[PDB]
Image 1 (cartoon, rainbow, N blue to C red):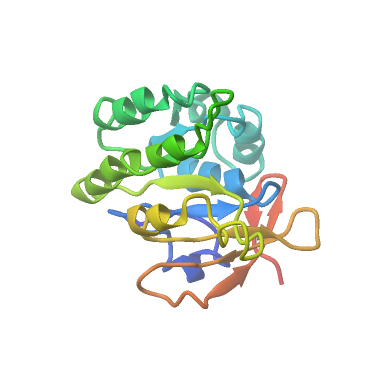
Image 2 (tube, one colour; image 1 turned 90 degrees about the horizontal axis):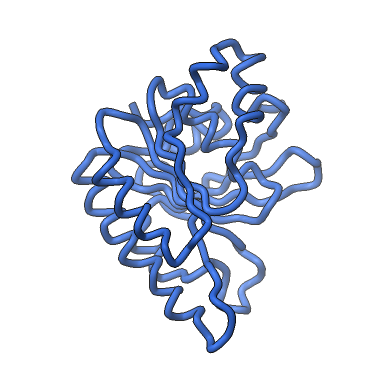
Length: 220
């Protein structure tokens, strides 16, 4: 197993992201950021660790999708182990804990994944650090543990100015090896994946798609 998905994406990704490595995903809101994480998991058979620190989690969205595609509600709920937090300084506690002290023979991991705030005195940088040690462990282990994770970052290619495009770049581009990206295109419900990094299957592989109310569908 690599991981599930669609086909418009599946072809692209090499077919299911990839084990051993973390496939970083950065883009804006309203793009399918979360809608993948879920679909990818409840259909990979068993347990996925899902760690959100903001919105994402949906015990309604999970059900609506397991409804129409055919599956099970009451049971599905217990797939993505019930984790967060919403205390980002104190997320390490959970990101370090959930890996070593939650693991077993199970599918994935998805995080949410970016910045946090204190109040003043310019924290930013100090926190722009955070993202490198969490991922240090979040890397050596994913490989050392033949497991695939999904790191949910933000902002994407805004332009080239304001530090080129990704949040903390150079780290993501060393800590995460498979850089994907979801951006919004003219259709409320239809974005586009473009592999910014990966091994097998060229970066120039820009694939398209559509998200419906049930999950990622292919188009025409």
